[PDB]
Image (cartoon, rainbow, N blue to C red):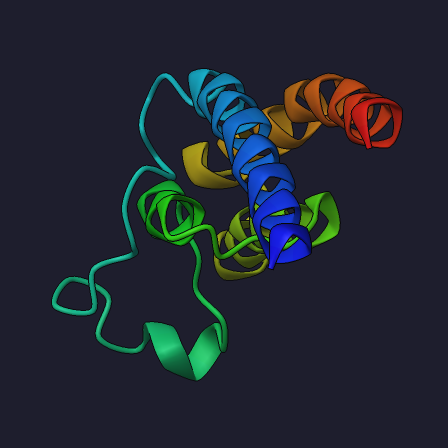
Length: 121
């Protein structure tokens, strides 16, 4: 159907905008603390602590399979990255502090992304 295609064009455009958001968010992590999944070889107990792990490479695979239907779903995943980190790591660690800074800096980017998704439809 022509409607299915139009729907697919919007998803593709959302995917384009989310890719740009993702790039901008990831620049706020120049240490690459959140680039890749936590290693279960190096943190064998991790899944006893964190039930839904997340990281920027895993978000990127979802993104490129057009697996985010809306900004809300994308934000859920970004928030997992931050929230998981702030639970597993103590307040006085480079990891926790890096999550706080990513959260604070990402807020600005996400605030405008929401306006652009609403605005462009």
